[PDB]
Image (cartoon, rainbow over all chains, first blue to last red; front, side, top):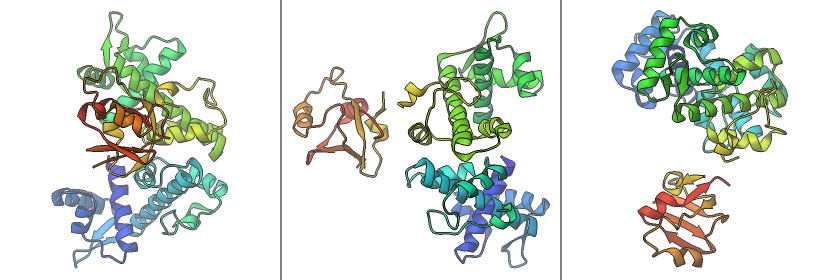
Length: 138
Length: 215
């Protein structure tokens, strides 16, 4: 799915960044169990969409819109993980894969509601903080 | 997405059925806001998939498999609706659309949990009863599948010793006090069962028949 794929690509990139890593197409490939030609196919579309630029050093620099989208997707991913552990009580071992799905179908409206209902949205159950809360308007 | 389109088509047929409407393609197309030609291509694709048959009247009859799936999708959809209003507090005017997306991503694991965390899952906030709860287990899973590579504790739903030809481990099980209703640690390694200090590494046939459900 075009958007879901792109949303996944940008979240992955965002993570690499978080990990102190350089977002390289090869990294995304092996991180997304992806085939190089495929990552190129996708990044290429993403580039035409103005979401990412492959720096002259062959690294991936997310354009401002790209980064805003990556952050939104990460925010939703983490608010999903919070709901899943805090409220639903889903197995901690199942929380991440479930959240990677929900990140594509959770609306901003649900996010704001969770910001209001969750006890703490500072960080995900996994230790990383929840980005973009300000941009959400919460 | 082929899967998501099918789930959506199946849930749509379920709603028309539930509304007392005939599941006709023109109806589904109107509902889904898709052209009749598209729904035709999708339903044909679903027939080859054995999910539906176009009856005499040109109505769509869901085969037992299509109905089982339609029911599951309608179940996640409504449980998502109860989660959205009962807990998240999402504007009632936005609960339907949100649920129609969430129905495709919610795992059964999340459903069994919601059933435990929600106050009442009889019907949706929209009046319709929540289907397939019995089939959600809210029998079990053949321990061969459920047996995770991680030593997890579960609950014996059924032993199925009547279908068993190899009675070798019948006492092995009794000795380890492993019976229906027993919480036992299962893990993939051959599959071993664990209870009352005694372990029971099962063989193929017993693995395919002992059915466990999450505690």
